[PDB]
Image (cartoon, coloured by chain):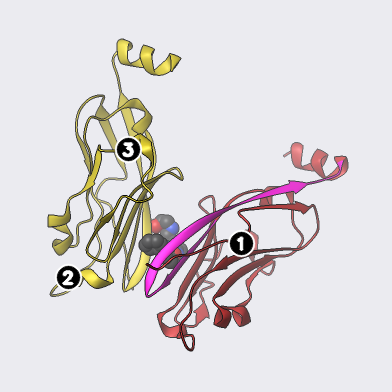
Chain colours: A red, B yellow
Amino acid sequence: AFTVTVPKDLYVVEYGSNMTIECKFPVEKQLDLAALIVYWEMEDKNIIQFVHGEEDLKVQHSSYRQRARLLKDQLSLGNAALQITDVKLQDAGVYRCMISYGGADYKRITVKVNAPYAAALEHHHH
Amino acid sequence: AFTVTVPKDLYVVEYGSNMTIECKFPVEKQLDLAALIVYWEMEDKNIIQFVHGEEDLKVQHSSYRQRARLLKDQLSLGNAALQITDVKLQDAGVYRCMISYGGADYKRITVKVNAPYAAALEHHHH
Ligand SMILES: Cc1c(-c2ccccc2)cccc1-c1nnc(Nc2cccc(CNCCO)c2)o1
């Protein structure tokens, strides 16, 4: 029974801080990047797609260019970690990590962003 | 290049009718049930999980208890079709057909429910 598990299903982050959200999956023996697909989406926006050993930038949403990365190194430990730098109020919401390695499964994580008045004000006047 | 395709991305169904929403994936030669995982979800509510050889109800959202089934027969033709019997207003929303058969992909399907006043009235209050 191939299962994806999330240590924390809810992260609370401060505006402008850095965030790492984890998804754990079981890895037997040595990791076979060829058979691994890691996909992170956030409310119908592709964040990262890791397939065939490499990330696909052709589909990455431009809002996450050069601020969202998968910690490729941690995949060998069965850890699919997404790191988003410079967290903004627009990053609050429901993330999904979908993994395909033998089986397939997925989990949802919720992110809340605390912000001072100033940052909230600019976000409000969109 | 593994693609899931949906003939219709929007279904309009009448309250109390039966609904089937189609989801296609490419299957060359013979289908390998061992490698197929089909997930149907509806706005972060799991409807069905088809893993290994048969669907798993272990996590089915109660709102779909005993009203949603996967048409196993058509999986061989690359058709992961979900059937909801006795469609209700709460079945309106965005469905997700997630499939892993070699590659992995998913498609969103939107469902609208037309209803007479009486059913709308009862749905509105409870
Ligand atoms: C469904 C899935 C699973 C999965 C499959 C079956 C059950 C549970 C999970 C696992 C890993 C990756 C994916 C996957 N799903 N596909 C991608 N990446 C992607 C990149 C760009 C665009 C799109 C399509 N966006 C919706 C419109 O088609 C998807 O990850």
Quickly name the residue at label 1: A7
Residue A112 in magenta stretch = yes
Name the element at disc 3. helix
Residue ID at (26%, 45%): B8
**Quadrant location, the N terminus of chain B:** bottom left
Name the element at disc 2. loop
Please determine whether, in this image, residue A15 is positioned above or below residue A36. Answer: above
Please determine whether, in this image, residue A84 is positioned above or below residue A120. Answer: below
Please determine whether, in this image, residue B95 is positioned above or below residue B79. Answer: above
**Quadrant location, the C terminus of chain B:** top left
Please determine whether, in this image, residue B22 is positioned above or below residue A51. Answer: above
Q: Say whether disc 2 or disc 3 marks the residue closer to the N-terminus.
A: 2
Give how far apart the Cα atoms at labels 2 and 3 are: 28 Å
* Mark nearer the viewer, 1 or 2: 1
Q: Nearer the viewer, residue B46 or B14?
A: B46
Image-quarter location of ligand 1: bottom left
Quickly name the residue at label 3: B64
